[PDB]
Structures are given as structure tokens and as C-alpha cells.
Image (tube, coloured by chain):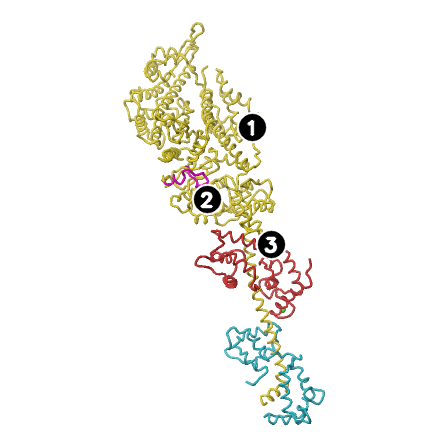
Amino acid sequence: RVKLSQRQMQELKEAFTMIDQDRDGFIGMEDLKDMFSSLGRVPPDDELNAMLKECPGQLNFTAFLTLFGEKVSGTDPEDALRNAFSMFDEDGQGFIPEDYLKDLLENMGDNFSKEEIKNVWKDAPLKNKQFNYNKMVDIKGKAED
Amino acid sequence: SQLTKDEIEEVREVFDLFDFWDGRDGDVDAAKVGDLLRCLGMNPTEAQVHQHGGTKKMGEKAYKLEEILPIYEEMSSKDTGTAADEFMEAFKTFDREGQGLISSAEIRNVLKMLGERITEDQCNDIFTFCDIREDIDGNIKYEDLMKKVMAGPFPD
Amino acid sequence: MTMDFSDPDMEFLCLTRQKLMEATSIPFDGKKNCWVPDPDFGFVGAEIQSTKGDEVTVKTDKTQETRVVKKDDIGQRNPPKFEMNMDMANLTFLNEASILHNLRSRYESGFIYTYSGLFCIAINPYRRLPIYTQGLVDKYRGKRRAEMPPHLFSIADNAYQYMLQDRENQSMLITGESGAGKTENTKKVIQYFALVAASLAGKGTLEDQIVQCNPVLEAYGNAKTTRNNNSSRFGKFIRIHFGTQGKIAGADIETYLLEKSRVTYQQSAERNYHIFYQLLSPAFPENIEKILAVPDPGLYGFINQGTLTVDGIDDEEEMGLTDTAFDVLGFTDEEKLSMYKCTGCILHLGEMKWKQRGEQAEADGTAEAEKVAFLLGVNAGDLLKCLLKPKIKVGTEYVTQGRNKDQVTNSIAALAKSLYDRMFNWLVRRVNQTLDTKAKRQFFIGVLDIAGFEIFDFNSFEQLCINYTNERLQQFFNHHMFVLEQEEYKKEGIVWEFIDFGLDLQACIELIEKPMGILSILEEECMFPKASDTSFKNKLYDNHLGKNPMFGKPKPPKAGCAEAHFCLHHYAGSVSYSIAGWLDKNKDPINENVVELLQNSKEPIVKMLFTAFQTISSVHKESLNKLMKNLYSTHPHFVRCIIPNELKTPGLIDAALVLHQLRCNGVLEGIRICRKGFPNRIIYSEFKQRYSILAPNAVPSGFADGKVVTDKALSALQLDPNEYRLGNTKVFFKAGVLGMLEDMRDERLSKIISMFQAHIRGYLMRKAYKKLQDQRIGLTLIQRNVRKWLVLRNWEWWRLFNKVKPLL
Ligand SMILES: [Ca+2]
């Protein structure tokens, strides 16, 4: 839980700050739509506000961390995840053999739903009906494709 | 009689691992009672495992932790599980010259032809794992084999 | 096996380490494999299928066939450890089948020698075998029996050691009929005492100075008997003498029990001695004329009663060799004549006819009488005179003329028999002269050859005498065995609880020789003029029927299948005898006058008849008593030559013929006795190494005492304390204990291997375990991170912060 490590919080410090400039630290309505300008994408009213709903009211940086109290829940650190995928990759990199991984998630450990399985297949980095884990680990945090 | 609190906690530990691997749901496929039991330190023969609930193919039967507990202690009632003493008198039945050496061709023959036959693969594995070498024809020390096998994969 | 299993000479004595290793590991299940009666091959190995009441169901091996054998007909077969076994005393299951197998299996693998307790069994190979090399002799010289594999040399050698060791005479009794090769064996035993005599350290050989005689002795002492073409009807003891250094000092032959009766009576498919049919053959016509006869055997009542010739026997050739040998033994052709003339004389005696007036018999032909009178060199007038009407005495001399017809004929047959008997003794005194060497004698190792136990479809007064003889011989053996097992049990401190084994045959022997016994009842009944095969019969019944276990009675057979009058239970089985004729066959009265008168003229006859009225049975008893008085004065050894088959061919076994000999042999009798004690005896060390697997313990094998181990393996098996006895160096087992033990070892060894395979299965899995734990942590981190991703991948903010920072 507090797993919101300093690396994660400080990272979130620079995040909440670029926006801000709002009357002494408050990611307000404008702070947001303004952001979506240098963001290169569309900003919708109602939604911009629906995002506020999530915290009691008024977003400093503290509440901004408390808001991310669903992000921490599972987030095992950076590397840890890559090593975890490693264990099922004998043939060094190029990665895991699709079948395996399916049987691995679908009917072993904490079984995956035939529905959770697809949510995963839709994106899943694949080729030669084989999986790409380092590219999947990347997607988790994501620095883009 | 009756297991202890710590004994139970132990079985549970091996148990959780096992049902985790065939799908965490509180059940372990019966075709895994022997492996399960081996992970608790025991060395059951296939006759013992079958007379206690093991099946051959998966998907047939399942056991909760509470059902396996009694199987574990019944199982552990038997005492001729085997001693160094016993394994030694047996190898000597085959020790032609009485030095403690036996052709690895023969031991492997024993292991794959006699008793509850073992697989070609399983024989190589245990020989590689116990690091037991054969010489020119200054073969295999069968006691070397016995001790390492009885000592387990994780010595120290 | 011994010395070097691979050494070349041992090819027909050992079996190679590998080949035996092989032979001892064939498949087996003491719980089903077994022995079963086979109408053809005596006994056969098989496996049990089912069971119910006293009706077992089985399946045989070599042929496959589900037969239904009764419970007391299933035979325990010995486990593989015992195959190709050297001494049948070691067998754990000692039944007939097992005896048959051990012997057969070894002969069918080229081995002819096998030990059975004291006996050394040697089956005829019917082909020269390397076995008798002066190279092998050295591989036996001085060694104690157990040091080397079975071999006749072993018994002969040890008999030689014992002689020099205990300084007492030795004897070797060798049994075996026709194609058993009994003579070769005696030959090779005598050769051996020779090789070792001059071995120590510094015109004719012994084996040949003696074999030289056999043609003559056999002409007068062998004959064809219902079941044997050449049967010695006398016993001969070849005593080979030695000096105080073990040096061969001489030899000689003493004979016993010549069957005179044959001289004047043959039954059906039999015939008198060989010589008679030899003389009357076309080889030496002159002789046939000096004898005063015509070459037609069938013309003399004393020769024609039975058969005229035998299959596979050439009389001319024999009369030839017989005569030739007569010269080699080196004896004046004039003596060689008398001998032939006396033989011839016996021919005519049987022709003399007699008629009577009231009760005084008289001649009728006078031609024969003068032929006999002459051949013997005496006056026919007188002969007829002292035969027809002699004269004896008081203070004066009366005419004992009592003689009638029945008395003279009989009186004459007696003469014939008496002549032959003296002729034979003399004939032996001669070879002995041919053998006497200058040397001094100190000890001797004699070899005995005697007619073995006989059982025909029709046994008469001749069979009884021979069986009576063997019975006392078997007893002799039983006793020797008794004295050694007693010494053995005392050597190991075990409790000996037995009465002399010899006594097991005393009842039969007593039923034959004690007052009121068969022979004595026969004798007394011989003194009653009107006695009959019926009065004698009833007097046997009166005296013994139902009054003695040994004496039984048969029952009327197949119309012609002769009527039996009583049966005795001999060690070789039960024999049924006919009584017809015994009263006639037994009379052998001496007629003083004929003797005094016969003490005249012709040189041999003087000597011969120069050296009451009795009987053949009283003389048999006397000769038998003497033979025995001599055997019990020596340390005996027993060889048993065996005829493998009717059709002289290598490697073939006739089951019934072999078993039969084993029962007459005393072999099956000695095993009967082993059964009653503790036949199996193992040294503690051999037991420890073979059965420790039955009660393992942590004490390292090299510190564990064998006896201590044996004791604990046995009680831990809760084995009946009645089945064994711990000695000072060995444990004594009864029948079948090792049978059980071997079966448990195989059982336990199989369970122990499964257990080891179990520990390996454990090791492999317990190692795979740690990998399984690591992979779990791994698959856990994956399943929840992928899941936490499936969420945030749509939560706007997650997206933002993902863009908001690449732009820092
Ligand atoms: Ca499960």
C-alpha cells in the first residue's frame, strides 16, 4: 500500500507541478484544460469535472497522492516484473511461447477469466504465435510503443 | 497420534503450493498426492500411494487440505520406508567382487527393469544430480549413490 | 565348483563362473513352481494354477498341459541357488523328483559325477571324456573332497589318505549293473592307487595284471539272468595291498557267495554259467571230444533248462578270449584240460538215469556213469556202488544203502554243484598265485563288486538270497552313516537323538536268518520226506503272517503271472516271492563215500576233493557272514555307477531306470535318513552374507559376527526352533528351511529396490519443488500486475501522468 514509493511520489510531484501554477498548488479546472493544450489532444467539459469527483474537493498534491490509492495497490516495482516473466522463458528473450502463457494464466495460479484473457490478447506483443514480455512490461508503466 | 499444529502448518504450505499450480481453489488433484507427499519429506512407493488415494490420470479426483492430512499421517504409519542398512544389503546382492563397485549399466538396469521401474530420463537425472561418476571401468560406488540420494537435492 | 572355473580340465567337472551364474538366476517362484509326476520322464517341473480339496490344478513347463494332480503329488522344487548342485545332501527339498532333477540336469550338461552324502554317483557318459588326466590327478591328489568338484578320484584319493592317516584297511563298494561301466571305474580306481603309490617323491601294470583275470572268472561266475545279459553270480573283493609308506605292495582276490544252484537249474529266460555254452561252441572241437560231448548245448538237462544263447553275445569268441586269458594267467594247458573236463563231467552227471525196485534205485545206461567215472579217474563200478548203495558204520560197517531214486538224482546234482564250487575256488587260488608279489603287505584298500538288489516279475529262492545279501550290505552302510553323523553332530555340539540307522533293516534281516525265520523253516522242512511247497508255505504263514510287519502276503495275478506266496519289505521296496521248488533247490547233501572215493586218481580231483548232509541256505549264511565280518573291519567308501538308459547313448536319461537303481542303490535310502535329521548345514559367514538382507542393521557388515547375525535373522523370522540348531561353526537346518529363506530374500530384495526407487522419486520431486515455489512468486506477480493494468489502462489520470512526464 504505502508502496507509493518516493520514486513514485516524487515522480508524481513533477507531474502535479507542471499543471498547477493554480493559486498556490491546486490542479484546478483551468490548470487541466490548459494542460491538454501542450498535450496535443481534446479536452471535454463535463469530464474535466468528472475527474474532480474522485477526490473530496480541491486537489493539492497530498490529495493527488491519495487519489492514486488504487495505482499503488498492485504495482510491484520496475524490474521485479521483468524477472517474474523471465522464469517462464528458457529460450532467452524473444520470449514466452503463447500456448504456455495462455495455459499459464488461464488455468494455473490465480486463473484468468476467458474474458480477462482477451483483454490481454487484444494488445499483447506477438509474433510467431509467441509472446514478448519485455515489451509487455514496458506497456505496464509505458514509455509508449 | 494426530498431527501437531506446526505439522499441519507444514502440510498446508506444501498443499497451498500444489493447488496453486493446478488452479488455486482449495483442491489438489489426486494424481499429485504422491508428489505432494514427497514434498513433505516422505518417500512413498507407488503401491503405497495407490492404496492411499492416488489415481493415475488428472481430472479424476480432488482433495481438500483436510482430506490430505489424514492420508499423510496414515501413510507415515509404515516404518519399513527403508534404511541405509537395507539399501546396502540390496546393492551387495549385485556386488560381484565385494568392493562396493557396480557397473552403472547394471544399477541402471536394476532401476529401470526391477521394482517399480524407473524412466530412462529419471535415471540420468539422479546420476547427474548426485554427481556420481563412473571411471574407466572403476565404475560407480553404490554407497556414494545411496548417500547422495538419501541426502537430497539441497544438501547444506 | 573349485579352483578355476575357467581352467580347461574342469570343462566336464565344473561349469564356468558365468555359465553357473547364469544357471543359478533363471526365473522362479517358490509359491508356484514345482515338481509333478510324469508318466514319461518320471517327474517334471510345473506351476500351480488353482486349488480345491485334495485336488490341485497345475500347468507344466517344457510341454504346457493343465493336469489335475493330487495334493500329496505336488513336489517342492529347489530354488535356483541349488541348480547344478554338487552334493544332493545340500538340497533343501530332498524328494525323489529333486534327486532325479539334480542328477539329470547335471548329466544333461555333460557332468557325470554327483555326490549324495557319502555316495559318489557316476553316471555312464557313453563316450570318452577328458576327466581322467594325470594332470587332473594332480588337481586332486591330497585334497579333501569339498576342495574340488565331484570326481571318482576324490573318493579314491581320500580312501588312500585315510589309510595312511588312520592306518586301517579301506574298502570301496561299487554297485551298478551292465552298462553302468562298473568295471571301467574299478579299473580307473586301481590305476589311481598306482599313480599315487609311486607318486610321493622318488611285465604288466596293476590294472592289467588284474583285468587279465576277468575273462576266466567271468566264464565260471557270470551268466545271463532274466534282466541282465552278463551277471556275476558271485562277489569278488579285489584287495590292493600297500606297505608302510603308502607304497603299492601287492594284490589278490577273495570271492564269496558263488550261486551253485545255477549249476543244476535255470529258470525260463536264463541259463547256466557262460563257460558251458562256450565249451559247446565251434572253437575248440577237440576239447568237445575230450569232454565226451557233442556241440549241442540243448542236450544236457543241467544246461538246457533255460535259454541256449543271449542277444549280443558271441560264445565262440568268448570261449576264445576265455581260453586265451587262461594262458595269459599262465597255466599249463593240461590243467586247462581238467578244468574243461570237470566242466564237461558236470554235463554227463545230469544225463545219468535212475530206476528203482521197491525203494532201492539202480542204474540205467551205465554209459554216463563210466563217462563221469573216467573224466574223474575213478572206477564206475565203485562210484555206482557208493551212489546206489554206500556203506558207513558203528563199530562195524552197515550198508547205508537206504538210497532210493529221489535220493540218488539229488545226491548227484549235489556232486555236480560240489565239483563246480571247488573248481571255482581253485580257479581263484590261481589268479592269486598270478598276483602274489615278493613285497610285504601292511594295509589294503579292497574293491567289492557284488550282485545288486534284484526284483523280477518272478522272484524265487535265488532272489531272496541276493536280496538278503544286499540288505546286510545296505545295513552296513546305514551303520557307517550313523557313526559319522554322530561324530558330526558332536563336533558342533548338537543333540544327537538317534538309534543306529542300521537297525532300520534288522527286522527284515532277522525275518530271514533267525531261528523260525524263513531260511530255518525252509531247512527243517527239508528234512521231511513228504514235505511240500504247501506244507512249507503253511509253516511260513503259521509262524509269521500277521505276526510280523515285514512279512506280508500278495494275491493271485494274471492267470499265467506266477503265484506269489509272500512278500518282504526290503530297503529297496517290497518284493513278492514264489515258494515253488525251494525244498528241492535247497537240498545240497554231502555224501561222504563219494568224497573218500573221489580222493583218488586224476591230480586235480585229488587236490579238489582233498582240501549232516547240508543245504544251500546254510552255506549262503556262512559265506555272507564271512563277507560281512570282513567289511566291518574296514573303513568303507561308496561309489554308485548308473545306467542312464536302455539304449546305450550319451546325455539321455531314462527316469524310471535311474530311480529304480537309486532304490536298489541305497542312495534313496541314505536320503531317507538325511530327511530324519538336519541335512542342511551352513557356515555362519555364508549365512550372514546370504541372508543379512532379511534383518539388516546399522552395524557395518565387517564387524558383525556371523553367528550373532544368523541367530537374529532366524528368530526375527520367528522360525520354529525345531527346524534348526545352532552349532559351533554352522547352523543345522531341516528340510525346506532354506527353501523358505531363499523365497523371502527374493521377496525382500524386490521390496527394497522399490523403496530405493521411491527415494529417487522423492529427491527428483523435492528438487523440482524449489523451482515450483520460485515460479509461483513469479506467476503471482504477473497475474496481478496484468490485472492492475487492465484497470488503469482506461483511468484517464493513468494516461495523463504517462504523457505529463515524458515531457519533464
Ligand atoms: Ca487447485
Kind of residue indicated by mark 3? Thr
Check if mark 2's residue and mark 3's residue have beta carbons within 8 Å: no
Report the amino acid beneath label 1. Answer: Pro
Which label sits on residue C549? 1
Residue C635 is covered by the magenta coloring: no
Is C145 covered by the magenta stretch? Answer: yes
Q: Is residue C21 left or right of residue C373?
A: right
Which SS class for mark 1?
loop
The colour assigned to chain A within the rendered structure: cyan
- The picture places residue A59, in percent across and down from the top left corner, at 69, 89
C171 over A13 or under it: above or below: above
Q: Compare residues C502 and C382 and report the one nearer the observer.
A: C502
Residue range corresponding to the magenta coloring: C135-152
Q: In the shown orientation, is residue C68 left or right of residue C190?
A: right
State the SS at label 3. loop
Ligand 1 neighbours mark 3 (CB distance < 8 Å): no
Viewer-proximal residue among C412 and C761 = C761
Identify the subunit bearing mark 1: C
Q: CA distance from mark 1 to mark 2?
A: 40 Å
Q: Is residue C95 above or below residue C217?
A: below
Q: Is residue C698 visible in this depiction of the protein?
A: yes
For chain C, the rendered hue is yellow
SS class, disc 2: loop
Mark 2: few/some/many CA within 10 Å (<14, 14-19, 20+): many
Crowd class of label 3 (few under 14; some 14 to 19; many from 20; radius 10 Å): few
Q: Tell me the quarter of the image containing the C terminus of chain C.
A: bottom right
Same chain assignment for discs 2 and 3: no
Colour in which chain B is shown? red
- The residue furthest left is C286
Chain letter for the residue marked with disc 2 in the picture: C
Which residue, given by chain and number where applicable, does mark 3 sit on?
B80
